[PDB]
Length: 293
Length: 293
Image (cartoon, rainbow over all chains, first blue to last red; front, side, top):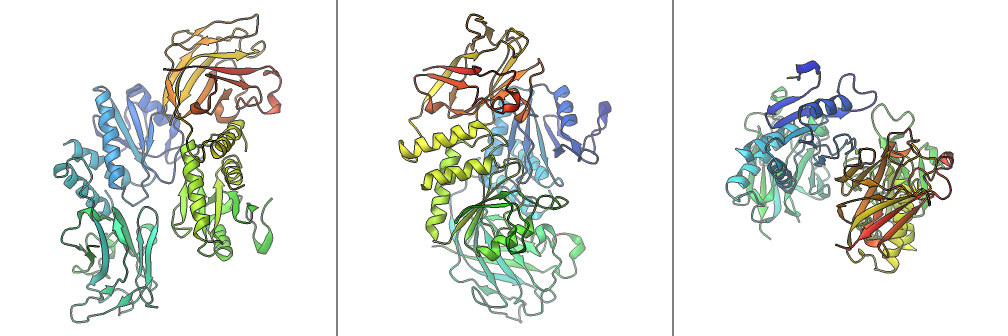
């Protein structure tokens, strides 16, 4: 819903009377099909003068603080990826402080790509005051659990150790045995664990054809703390989608209950898209088994 | 000095046997004249396999941690601007830890623009182990002072308030009175103070034509702490250079001695370039007057 009022042609989305969403305001030979930085600057200067903050939720692009009168905060969110809960808490904290300055402070939120990052961090603010991928949905769920239970603060810090990964309904995906997935565990932009199933060196494969599980014994698993990314790379032509991976996870280990995490086919970032509902059947899922150090 | 060895055409600079400087590795429709991300990844994978870390000193653009096998740290340095001393200490600690991890570990350093930020942050490591604008030079000097006196730590935290700004040898620059400069004080991407001399509202102008001084009473100046940037905006057609401003500063308030900071014509970001040595004469300068709260 482009903002076509008052002679404007920006890709804005006036989500709430005090919260504005838009796309990345670009400069140079990129204003033809995207927002021009100066035009949107003028738009939000003639509407709210010295009463806006521009949240640039881009870990990959930034323009200058000076354009928006040096009121710009950058949240390092990767495309199709979630922010850390510390990032979400700091985000909502600075937003609440901004709205406490006076009654007519608005906020502009954008990201370079689609309304995944801006959607996530506008819905997060929406439910704090009251998305594309299911990782963002589950992170909004994490933030609501924090908001209503562990009041606007970090959960009880749990350091968990992952011990095995169970894959449900593997008949159809992969070569046929499940020994093609590649594991990558990322914590704070750091690859803390990787393994390849075909070589079977850092992990072992124990396929049980009775229940269609190819549970992989994940020896000496990392003691993950905080937000974790687990992507599954494959070498058998799986339908790679977002961020060039068959499917990836994003979760906070402080929210895991009873040291078990199962992600249904629908959560499972990338299989959730309906266009690939033929290699991942309805019962497809990945179960993560945890341990307490 | 581009790296033409081993069939490569990269814009590298092998500064030391274990430190590498290069330009930003770009992707998309930019590899025609800039560094291709995949090509540089291949170069530093076949040269240093799993024994390097790439430092991205760009506050305006980043690509993805995944390309360099999730060994990438971003330092938020603005173009034609200096890093914070906390950032410099964190970077130097990171480099020291990386080199202590193994005897083969290398570092790759780049920035999007010219070799100002990469030059700054490579000379900082060069002086710790053993530059475009002069503020980067003064910050390398700040780091050498910290390294050799207040050993590799911050100096005694000093917070001071600017009481007035003295402009030396103004006969020729500006309208002829000095009532065209505009002040902008930026601390941690925050416009903490601004003023316009022509209106004479936030500051008062006291032109002392006897000594060619237009010292401006900076009433109720900010209580600055840490790293401060001071840009001088003008509306009399000054030869705007870097950052689109007549001249700006970048100074740490902890390093001020005797509560005074005079900036000679040579330091004075933008007057430093000899092409403008006709409106800023040899005695041009700015003096920062401080007061202890």
